[PDB]
Image (spheres, rainbow, N blue to C red):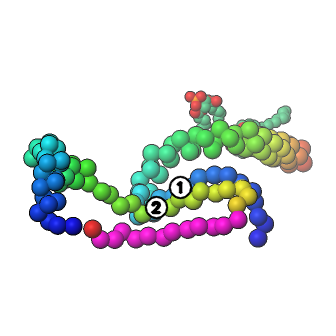
Amino acid sequence: VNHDELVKLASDAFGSVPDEDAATSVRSLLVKEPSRFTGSYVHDRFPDASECCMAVAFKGAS
Amino acid sequence: RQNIPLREILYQLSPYQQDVIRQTFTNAPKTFLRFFKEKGVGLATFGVLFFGIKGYTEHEMHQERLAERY
Ligand SMILES: CCCCCCCCCCCCCCCCCC(=O)OC[C@H](COP(=O)(O)O)OC(=O)CCCCCCCCCCCCCCCCC
């Protein structure tokens, strides 16, 4: 792929997408509804299953 | 170890994500009244039988002591 030709093709094709308001950016949405980690437990029991799948995770890094 | 067929979803919360003894003060009068509502009849029939038979026996013993007097 050539960079200049892809620039020209993208400006012709994808040039009409709307811009973004500053108040509705990705960072504002991340601040408005943040992630919360809760230490908890769930199992989904089945009466006649064969396998036993399980995952244990800790709160990791962004 | 005794396979049990069952279908469920179980949820559990960490013991460091909830309180320990704060609800114990709210539920204490209700639990007191519920305990006496559940065990009221048995405790009452126990008390009636024990104290009635004891009182009748002690009364008749006192009458027996009085009958020996001159
Ligand atoms: C002459 C010698 C004199 C001696 C004087 C002292 C005698 C002992 C002290 C007085 C005891 C009397 C009151 C006792 C109260 C205790 C608490 C209680 O009963 O609650 C439990 C109980 C509590 O239930 P709960 O709160 O549900 O656990 O109360 C009852 O259910 C009521 C019990 C009533 C039944 C006993 C009544 C007294 C019996 C006397 C019988 C006399 C017969 C006479 C026959 C001959 C006639 C010629």
Q: Which residue is mark 1?
A: B11
Q: CA distance from mark 2 to mark 1?
A: 8 Å
Crowd rating for badge 1 (residues with CA inside 10 Å; few <14, some 14–19, many 20+): few
Q: Nearer the viewer, residue A4 or B33?
A: A4
Label 1 secondary element: strand
Relative image position of residue A2 (x, y in whole percent): 17, 67
Residue at screen point 78% across, 40% down: B45
Q: Nearer the viewer, residue B51 or A50?
A: A50
Please state the chain letter of the residue tagged with numbered disc 2 in the rendered image. Answer: A
Q: Which residue is mark 2?
A: A40
Amino acid on which disc 1 is placed: Tyr
Crowd rating for badge 2 (residues with CA inside 10 Å; few <14, some 14–19, many 20+): few
Vertical placement of residue A59 versus A20, above or below: below
How many marks on residues?
2
Please state the chain letter of the residue tagged with numbered disc 1 in the rendered image. Answer: B
Residue at screen point 74% across, 38% down: B41
| Part of the protein shown in magenta | A50-61
Vertical placement of residue A52 versus B31, above or below: below
Query: In the displayed structure, does residue A42 sit left or right of residue A16?
Result: right
Q: Is residue A26 magenta?
A: no
Instruction: Answer whether residue B55 is visible to the viewer in this image.
Output: no
Check the picture and name the quadrant holding the N terminus of chain B: bottom right
Residue at screen point 48% across, 70% down: A56
